[PDB]
Amino acid sequence: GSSGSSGDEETKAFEALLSNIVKPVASDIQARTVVLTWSPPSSLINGETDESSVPELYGYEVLISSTGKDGKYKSVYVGEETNITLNDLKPAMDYHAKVQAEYNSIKGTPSEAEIFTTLSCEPDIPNPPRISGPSSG
């Protein structure tokens, strides 16, 4: 049932909205597994449209370049959820990551890169980078 153009106006808003998210943050980083948490894109519709309308299934894809941000990116996971755990990674390594949004067959631009270092197969890291409030000096 291919007719042709289907309300392009919508496609545009998606090209910008889907590309209006924030770089994924790395937490509870482990040997090869890690906790990647990212927030949804910000709608610039200006409220012109209802609030309980915008979709929340923005297919987010996690990209990583064990080599570097100036090389090739590989897919590790792909879903709608916001928080996901990575796997099949390399311990004692340092690479960048990014999350791209895609909805209605519309692939937008990924967010900034998030460099995160993983621990070694064995229990080395003493404690996580977690910060417990500010500290004088």
Image (tube, grey):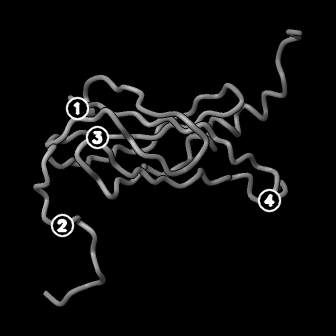
Looking at the picture, which amino acid does disc 4 mark? Glu
Which one is earlier in the sequence, the residue at label 3 or at label 4? 4
Q: CA distance from mark 3 to mark 2?
A: 21 Å
Q: Are marks 1 and 2 in contact (CB under 8 Å)?
A: no
The numbered mark at residue 98 is none
- Which residue is located at x 39 percent, y 52 percent? 35
Dot 1: what SS? loop
Label 1: few (<14), some or many (≥20) within 10 Å? some
Q: Quick one: 129 or 39, which is closer to the camera?
A: 129
Q: Are marks 4 and 1 in contact (CB under 8 Å)?
A: no
Which one is earlier in the sequence, the residue at label 4 or at label 1? 4
Quadrant (top left, top right, bottom left, bottom right) of the C terminus = bottom left
Q: CA distance from mark 3 to mark 1?
A: 7 Å
Depth check, mark 1 against mark 2: the one in front is: 2
Which one is earlier in the sequence, the residue at label 3 or at label 2? 3
Instruction: List x then y, in percent, for residue 46.
Output: 74, 58
Q: How many marks?
A: 4
Q: Is 89 left, or right, of 107 in this rendering?
A: left
Q: Quadrant of residue 93?
A: top left
Label 2: few (<14), some or many (≥20) within 10 Å? few
Q: CA distance from mark 4 to mark 1?
A: 39 Å
Disc 4: which residue: 51
Disc 2: which residue: 127
Disc 3: which residue: 96
Q: Quick one: 121 or 111, which is closer to the camera?
A: 121
Which one is earlier in the sequence, the residue at label 1 or at label 2? 1
Looking at the picture, which amino acid does disc 2 mark? Asn
Looking at the picture, which amino acid does disc 1 mark? Gly
- Which residue is located at x 40 percent, y 33 percent? 63
